[PDB]
Image (cartoon, rainbow, N blue to C red):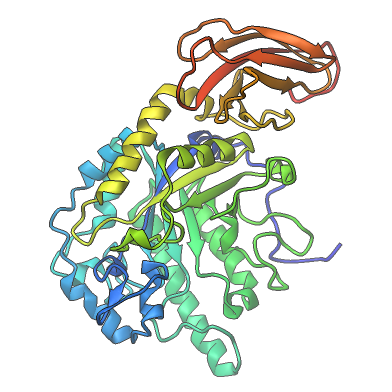
Length: 445
């Protein structure tokens, strides 16, 4: 039992309506947009395979010369209403936007630095326009914010002298100033998702992370803050030295989701995964043939996976320099939206069902105790195994899309075969189960 001033604050999951909304949303989109979209992974003739948003680093570009990319920031095809229509049609209930990435360029007209949209040919407050457009479509907006900033000389990677400490202190002042600014210009913000918080400097300043969390919660009622922000008194990040989760939800699982058999611990807190369509490209990269690019079904599989274990999933997009989306991303959003329109009752506002994982796919649980079977892998046996928790029985099964009744055969105490539909749906599909919890056997139902 280690005593701590800047360790965890929340007892269990938050159950206030704004957290319920953050959670019930389930499906988000990420936007990574900034100066990196101009060179798109290429610099001085060399195409770099690393993440396009890190190209300043891959190509060893000095800050002064990286930031002169602002002179070419002119996204004439940008239209925030079109971006919000795209998100709505994909079935997202929220969008997270890079307000400022590591390069330090701000997508709003910050009064605290010259490296902003204000000082580009385009001049306009892109951040404000997107906030309005998404909110007009009924889509919540979350702000990604990089603490690490390659544009501000005051930033330190570690505190190695009194000078470093004085310097980093003003940098933290500067960071609070931008945070207050985003919270006061854009009060409909629902979440701040921090990044670039892993350096020794930040870990040494745990108190500052707790302060930022508190500051923003005073400024924006109900606002959510990701675990990635937080370091405790010992420099321990995400979960404090007593294993307790800091911030409002766990953020991680980029490129590997929690294991549905081994990582059931995650159902005990709120959490959010974010993913890329290629293997590791968040900002726009001009050449997607360099790594594996996920198909719509592989993405939909990850989204349902997340919801089945009590978490959110956010699919990333890296808009072109011009303010439009490349065709792969338009195809992806469309394909996702088509499936979500059909099967979304087993994703939106669903949660962990407390059933043993089976091979055919994933269970999710609705707000009224519906139990959905989302089938990704069709058994040649024509039978979907359903093993129930103690005291739970399956009274009915129904194909979601048509309401057709589906046979359920009991095979042992607590196990059934649910038949596959008479006609193969030809895509990942949903069977809704009606279940009954027996009088006073303890269970989550």
